[PDB]
Image (cartoon, rainbow over all chains, first blue to last red; front, side):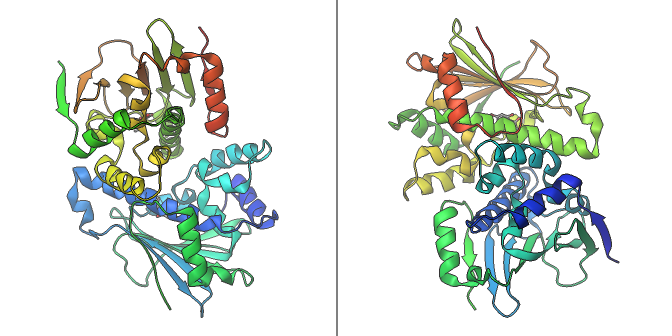
Length: 208
Length: 208
Ligand SMILES: CCC(=O)c1ccc(O)cc1O
Ligand SMILES: CCC(=O)c1ccc(O)cc1O
């Protein structure tokens, strides 16, 4: 059923640093995740140029932001390329061992955490606001998996027996009890206007 | 021998706009190309995690900047993943039809040309300083090709019968007669310090 994995030592370190370093500009987490979704959307778009049957699983390419105040979650859904099980396990598709090394070396050279996505490890900036991230993903090659962590050096992967999604990745952020501002419609609008105003796919902010 | 292709109408338009729009901050072209090389280097690195024989063609991952004042060229060499012939033809691996659409829509909404790489069409910013770009590339799956354009709505692809390179892509910029500043060691250093100081692969500026 549930398989448990250890983060590579470097990714464990990165995460600890994101959770432990005092850093007020937490909002950048949404830019990082939107831009991840935008990159995955490019990949399914590039691939459908040569093989247009890859879109049999969803012809519409978009990003949705779903806050839910009861569950204290913000969900970023994209209909991008999705991850195989192998991708999930290899640090959600990233070059995370050397991306972290490069990042922790930019840090001790005049850079701040906001430059995280330049090293290809943006996803972990989710840990700025979330106490637990759950990642549901579906690639055309493979079945649907749920990936999950509350940091602490381990993550779980299970085949997700719940709701089919067709193709893409849903990042569910279970927010820290003091970061509920990121559930407010006004707050989300502002961040999307400020950090992601020129992203080439519809972004849709759901209402409650 | 030499096959000639037509740029897609949108890419033709983008290029014309890059060549024709008055825009003084031409230097951003080097940031765009370095960051393309860095992305390709990530791809061969991600792929060698699962299959370490993909590095049989070059174990070292780096970017080199080679000015040559006699030929009036600046060459950006990377040992990244390389392009197949198909990739070369599909707009050098980019989503260029819709990336341009997204870009030309950011333009008439408060954005300037420097935001070009956010739409995945950074490569064409080469036309800010070059009268002709020649692209030599080698992917592990395929042979070695030269791709070439002086804009005007057409590009050529030939199998490159010259010097083997092992794996990667070399972008040769044949500079406009008034943009030779980009051949100066001081000028290149400054741009690399200002726009690309935290890129996670060695960048080496060759000397003449
Ligand atoms: C591999 C690309 C992918 O599916 C993905 C990864 C991280 C993320 O925050 C969003 C995504 O869509
Ligand atoms: C497909 C990635 C690739 O080989 C490449 C493309 C454009 C570029 O300026 C440099 C590159 O290395």
